[PDB]
Image 1 (cartoon, rainbow, N blue to C red):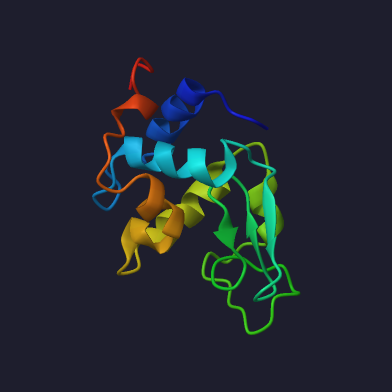
Image 2 (tube, one colour; image 1 turned 180 degrees about the horizontal axis):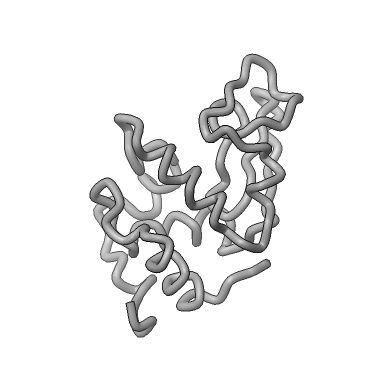
Length: 130
């Protein structure tokens, strides 16, 4: 499913992402925008290390979910990576929450540093009623 901006904004808020571990909703919106373009079926194979990024937040199979083919991987979210490709994003959200409970926080995603950190991210939630 490809979410519309405000549609996703409202959904994330209801799932309790606003301010989760100090991360504003606008930051989560910026992250999903640059990782998948708000697309839940997005997948990306990293030929360099044999891992795959799954779903709306492009969560990596080496640490967060199990896909069985990634060498020396763990499954910290205790989820099949398949769960991160559903239209309902409840599981992807529960896993993103797990990722940021680690010391790096939102910085775990390099794309966040390049495209979101120290920027005016208001634009991602403006006019959405959240």
